[PDB]
Amino acid sequence: NPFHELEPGPEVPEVVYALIEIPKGSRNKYELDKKTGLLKLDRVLYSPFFYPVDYGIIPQTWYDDGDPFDIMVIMREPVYPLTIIEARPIGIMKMEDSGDKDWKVLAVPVEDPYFNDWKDISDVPKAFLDEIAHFFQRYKELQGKTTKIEGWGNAEEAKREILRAIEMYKEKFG
Amino acid sequence: NPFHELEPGPEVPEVVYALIEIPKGSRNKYELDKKTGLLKLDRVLYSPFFYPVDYGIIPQTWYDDGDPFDIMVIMREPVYPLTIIEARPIGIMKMEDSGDKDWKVLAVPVEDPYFNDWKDISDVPKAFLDEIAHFFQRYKELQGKTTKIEGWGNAEEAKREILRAIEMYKEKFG
Amino acid sequence: MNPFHELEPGPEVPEVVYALIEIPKGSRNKYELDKKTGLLKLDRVLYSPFFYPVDYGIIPQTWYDDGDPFDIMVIMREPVYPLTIIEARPIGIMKMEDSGDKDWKVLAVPVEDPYFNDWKDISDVPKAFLDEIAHFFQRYKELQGKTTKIEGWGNAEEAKREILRAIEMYKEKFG
Amino acid sequence: MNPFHELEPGPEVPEVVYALIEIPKGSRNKYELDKKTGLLKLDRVLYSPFFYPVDYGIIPQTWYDDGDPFDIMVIMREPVYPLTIIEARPIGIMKMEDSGDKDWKVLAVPVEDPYFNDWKDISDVPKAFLDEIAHFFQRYKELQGKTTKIEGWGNAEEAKREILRAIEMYKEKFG
Amino acid sequence: MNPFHELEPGPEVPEVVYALIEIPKGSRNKYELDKKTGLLKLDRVLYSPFFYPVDYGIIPQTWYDDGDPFDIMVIMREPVYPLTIIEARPIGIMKMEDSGDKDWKVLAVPVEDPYFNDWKDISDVPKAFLDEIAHFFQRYKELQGKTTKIEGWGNAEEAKREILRAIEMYKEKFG
Amino acid sequence: MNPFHELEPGPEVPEVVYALIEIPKGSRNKYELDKKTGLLKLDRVLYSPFFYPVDYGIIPQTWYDDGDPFDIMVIMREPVYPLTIIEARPIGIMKMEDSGDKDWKVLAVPVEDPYFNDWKDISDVPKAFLDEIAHFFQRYKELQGKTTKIEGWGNAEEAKREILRAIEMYKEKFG
Ligand SMILES: [Ca+2]
Ligand SMILES: [Ca+2]
Ligand SMILES: [Ca+2]
Ligand SMILES: [Ca+2]
Ligand SMILES: [Ca+2]
Ligand SMILES: [Ca+2]
């Protein structure tokens, strides 16, 4: 299982690995099968929305909601599921999903020179942050779930949470 | 301008023409330029939603909101903008957009045998009607606009509104 | 690790099975699982300009009369990637023979797409869609000189019966 | 207006003709020119999961024995959009009958794609590719109960002669 | 009707112009407007495996020093279809010469995508993106034996200046 | 595990080899095998708007002068997914140097696509296509300031000899 075998990053927390589960533009929500590590269909979103970013997890992390720590990587061309990307955290989306702390790192790929000058949350166009928050605010509405979006934190805050999640993993597993 | 030159349908109101502006899966919202009849970008949706149906207008119609009557055609493979489809109305979505009556016909293509037994609103899976209503409920949320979804009418009601819109066009233009 | 051998046939057999997808809807490339390694392998490029009309794969830990894992076709609105696991509800079975071999294939819908919540048996599928699937398997190997015979469609109960047979066959051959 | 009537048959007929594309390679939707309106119109969704193996259209200002514009079928590496004009070199012709009507089709390559610079006649096309095109037309209307008959392929010389005949037929019937 | 002649250069020249798109981002096919009819036409297939990095088109009712309509590149997140009109804000201009011809091209953002609300001048564009556009035009005709010289980028004010020049040139040649 | 170490070089080397695909035709993303992890990893986004003109990968259990697995580049009509195995016939070899290192690449066609049945050597490939591949490799790292040198193409005989040498080098370095 790639979640357990891969390190959290080559230079934590400045550069982490993102293990992508869902490419931008997908309406299918994929997850990793915990037994086998194969990709598994979790569900088809109930609404005609698509993931606005490549979406995945940071290996060897664990979070308050009892899952690996989520990461969103802005890719110009989406990658395939189960692709590793070297990513620089630039911010963090604060949200609760049904009372669980479900925060998500926002990151850019180190190896696309397009994003060389994106280093903090203030470098992202605000319409783009709004569209991401709106997606998570409404994507489970027809399943009757409520999500609360609490805002965006900056790069420093993102990196602190990554360190916290790396420590939580070490506790729970070994 | 195709809006003025084409008849409303070969067998109104059982079979109408749909002039498609937006193929299913588009985030770009297109309209017809009224001067030239060329396709024009109206806007990019502010949220990562895609049109869940091929979306267009019925030629030579006019509606209470001061626009051609809208029609949504369920296509398995989306068509290109400015394509004419022969469509059978099977229902109607009732909604208001900023206080304007903005109802939209739901239809299936006559020439796809997949839909041969779809003749009324009750033949559509309810999750699919929900996803369409949810799209129109939220797609302008970040533009600060409010839309109210009032429910779905059946095929007979759709066909009555089509006749009304065909008459309204004749009044206003000639 | 070979997914075919390592995954259970499903979480609630035969009402819900796992489909391990090999070929997404819309592909002209026909992929298979490499027997030795479990990697995806190109079997062939179809000789005609036809595309797979459904997401196509196998049920893990099954064996059928034709000497292969039992095939399953899953109706997906948006195709998945190869090697994706889908929890699927069987709703019917296509009966066909390919060069003397019984090459029947389960038809299924995904449990986690609410669009298909009411599809529970073969009669819930538009007839034109069943015909398009059957026509595909009737003709897709015509230029390879192969003849296939479509024998018709069986219902959900029959599909479930055959899944149980295939699971038992696997146990006898490998277990 | 109607591009079918407004555009010349080609800049150097019959060596180079215009192909007015109606259906891009890969489409399961079959489009046709209103022929009175001029705008693209959905004729049908193919009943089988087959896709057009070439970019398909008509030569402007032509008329053929079947009572329609002359079908041309251009090999493109990347498909174009409907209503795009391509300068095309005829390299052959598919002889077929559809419902008894002579429904022959020109096969051509784009002048402005150097990939095909050395394709000049029907013998330059891989045989498997000619077979895939013929098989598509043999079977694409099978579920509609129509019968087509594939009679074989003619060479570039024959295709060019037929183009000139179609140009003459248009003049007699309209001009 | 020919869109190039019938549409105004824009609703609020030179702050907002119309871009009539001929080539969507991601295309290897290079399309143009047919001079006589206004239909889309394949100009060529690029000789190298490069794709247009931006949606590419022309400003209606303009004429430039190189004897063609003035070209405009629009940065779109999702590409449009050919012959689509986009209201665009010019933010810069690429200066380049193609075989002795001044072939400068306006860079613009769509007015109706809020993603670009803060892009108002050449300095707002990531440098790597400008380089990728320039590299494309530097090399895309290399195998055709053509040499192009990239002279650099001008700012929004310069782009607007040139748009006004191009509008005047059109009036003098056709009006 | 790591498919690079687990899979044989081919079922009938050097006439038929396995190509383990890392990058599908059309990708601007350059992927590489963790080579220790085994999972697909993004190496870089190409700095220019170029796309891989072929499906690109490596031959398992090979090692080459450049200190990596032997690059193979399979002509597919429909691209495959990363980590797919294709049975491939070598028809030639591209000789090139990258940063001074001998970075030669096998060119191959799939055994199971009848379209390429008559492609057996480098002379069977359209010259424009060989030029497009070479131009891609000549220029794709230009904005990274790297220099590559294209030295030309060898025939099938030469490609096969090099495959055997690479198989031997792997054995010496690992086996
Ligand atoms: Ca979480
Ligand atoms: Ca309306
Ligand atoms: Ca089977
Ligand atoms: Ca015909
Ligand atoms: Ca120019
Ligand atoms: Ca190498």
Image (cartoon, coloured by chain):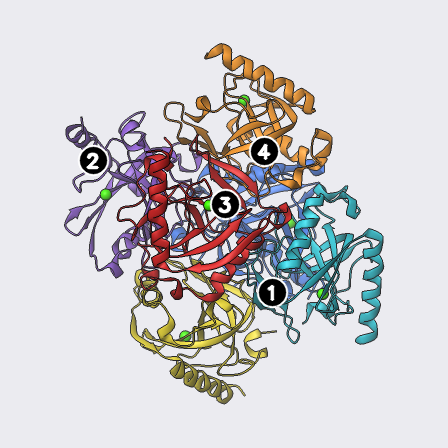
Chain colours: A orange, B blue, C purple, D yellow, E cyan, F red
Label 1, on which residue? E31
Q: Residue at x 69, y 21 (%)?
A: A156
- Identify the image quadrant of residue E40: bottom right
Measured as percent of width and height from the top left, residue D24 is found at 48, 62
Label 4, on which residue? A73
Please report, as a chain letter, where disc 4 is located.
A
Which of these two is toward me, D99 or A154? A154
> B105 left or right of E120?
left
Q: Amino acid at mark 1?
A: Tyr
Residue C143: mark:
none
Label 2, on which residue? C63
How far separated are the C-alphas under marks 4 and 1? 34 Å
* Placement of the N terminus of chain E among the 4 image quadrants: bottom right
Mark 1 element type: strand
Q: Residue at x 64, y 22 (%)?
A: A158
Measured as percent of width and height from the top left, residue C133 is found at 31, 50
| Residue A65 in the image: above or below residue B38 | above
- Identify the image quadrant of residue D161: bottom left
Measured as percent of width and height from the top left, residue E174 is found at 79, 76
Q: Amino acid at mark 2?
A: Trp
Label 3, on which residue? B154
For label 2, count other residues whose C-alpha is less than 10 Å away and answer few (under 14), some (14-19) or many (20+). Answer: many
* Placement of the C terminus of chain E among the 4 image quadrants: bottom right
Measured as percent of width and height from the top left, residue E104 is found at 75, 61
How far separated are the C-alphas under marks 2 and 4? 41 Å
Please report, as a chain letter, where disc 2 is located.
C
